[PDB]
Each structure stands twice: as C-alpha cells, then as structure tokens.
Image (cartoon, rainbow, N blue to C red; front, side, top):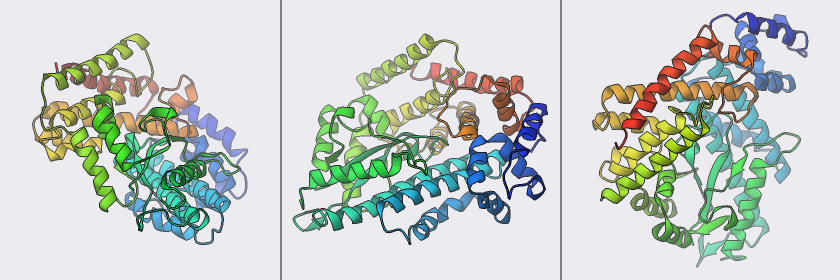
Length: 429
C-alpha cells in the first residue's frame, strides 16, 4: 500500500466531510480510508450498511472465503418465504460479498487469481441458489415436479465465457444457456416459465438493485429462439449446424451447481466431440486463420484505442491464442480441455506448444490486464473495458496497481500488450 498521491488526498478530503455515522474519521483504519478513496461502489455500499466496513476489520477476507459462500447464503435464505424475499436476499448477498471482494482486490490482500475465483464462485452460488428455490416453488405451484415417464427432470444451466472459465469480470453480465433432459404440465412450457422467473429474479432492478444482468443471446437460435431446449434439440443443433465460432465459445461452457449425474454427463458428452475434434485437417486450420483475420481486421479498423479487452494485445487476443491451441490439440491432449485460461496456458507450456518465454509472458500479461480491468470496474461497479480519461480515475488505478503514476502504468501495460501482439501475429502463421 503506497500512501495516496496528491489527487487522491484532495479527493479523500472531500469524502470525509460527508461520511455518515457511525463512520467518523476516528473509527477508520488506514486501509478503510484508501478503499473508500479508490471505490465509489464501496463508499455507497457501506453508507447503507456500515457494519460491512466494521466487519472487514474484525475478520479480513481470506482467499479461500468462497468455500463458505453457499452456506452463508443458505443461512440468510432460511427465513425467506416468498419470491420477493428471495430477490431481496440475493441482491443483498451479491452486494455484500462484492464489497469484500473489492476490499481484498484493492488492498492486494489476495492474488488476482483468487479474486477471479471469488467473483466466479459468488456468481455460481447465487445462480444455483436462485435456481433451486425456483425449481421447488414452480413444482409446488405449477403441475408438480415435471418428469419423463416417472423420472424428475432438472433445469441445467451452462455458464459461458469468463463465468464458465471461472475468471469472471468484477462487473459482468452472466451469459447463460438453459436446457432440460427429457411432462407434467408439459415439460417445455414448464421450463420456459421457470427460465423466465429465474432471469427476472437474477436481473430485475428493484429497490435493492439487481444480482447480475443476464444475457441469454449465446443460446442456440440466438435472441429469437426458445429460452430453454431439450437435450435432443440441443444435441441436434450442434451436431448439424454447429460452427467453429460456436466450438470456440463452448470451450468455456461449464455446468453451474452439481456437475455429476446421468444428465450432467450426457451434456458433457455432447460437447466433447463437438468442441474437441480428434482429427484436424487443413480446413480446420484455415478456419482458425480466417477467425484470426477477422479479429485483426476489427482491430485495424477501430484504430487507436484505450480498450483493454478489444485493443491489439488485449484480453480478447490472449483468450483467442489459448483457445486456438485448445481447438487444435485438445482432442488429443486432455490437459487442454480445461475451461479456465490460466491452467490451459500452463499446459500449453508443458506440451511445448509455445516456448516458455512466450507462455510466461502471456500469463503475466493476462494477470496484469485482468487486475487492471477488474480494479477499474470496481471503482463504480460498471462494465467498462476502456482506460479512464479523467485525472482522478487514472490516479486511482496507478495507486492500486502498486505503481507511482499514470504515464508509468501505461508503459508497463503497453509492454505487456506488445508481447501478446507478437504471440498473436505468430499464431498459426
């Protein structure tokens, strides 16, 4: 923790003459002040729930805290009777844990890798608790537990992108896909209705805010098609119409909740031969080259940019590099079938698919970029991918990235992106 810079000192002075009871300046540790100075999101959250900042000193957050999320949430949902009570608690819990994550990340009390796990597990935990509670309600309300010839049918959810990969952004949509395996009230209508209530419970702004903005657009047949599909229809779609951009996306797909059952297993079985082909020819490699060209043309087109995600050498190019190796060799190398980028990168190094120089530079660039973007997002809990233009937020980021000033932060960033762009250009050359 490098003491606050001139601009952060002038801003903190505007925050103190404004802080509510019981948060007077004398009841505040040196870290509490730096976190409040860094994040308007944490400020606003602790104004309404002052206990939270008080409870962050009586028990600071540990890396493995995510192992308690599900039990903490089930305890808070013990005295919940109706949907409005479910929604209220999911919202409160998300905000409460998010504050603790912002706390840990701001002060570097745990590593970014552990922040990534905390964010992803929080989201998993909330999705699953929501789904479980609504399954029960919909069964008790609408025509009993839905079945197929006696056997009860569950709702399965795939988390996609960074959620599936266990590397969620600090302020993020959750991209999901809904499916059910095999009637009572008719299975298809039942799960559509439940799917609608689930999206509402997670995403509807109330007086307590929302849990996550939900994005269902990656599902088969896009925004226009059904909200939930049977396994048969899921299977048919990918086997018959599935394309390489879809294989790329499905590298990340992970079942939320318990991934262990006859149904969880048929799903994983559909995806394995689709994503990870065992036989690769020139047409597969050229497809990947064309996808690479499309990214490179998009970059060239947008020109000079402060976008950390889409810029040349950005997060999206690292994901592309890694997933390209997974699509080529994953079928023959089980270590490249992981949903998470960083273990994949480790396997890429062990297999000598990249040099150690290249692989370690990619890992370090990835963690720098993710820390930088997730810190930035935690300032106001917004989904921004672009570096700030204003002096306060630039000053804020430099300080939190263990650096001295903004010119130097951008120099270190520029050097990491240069390494990524070199590896990206050499990729399937």
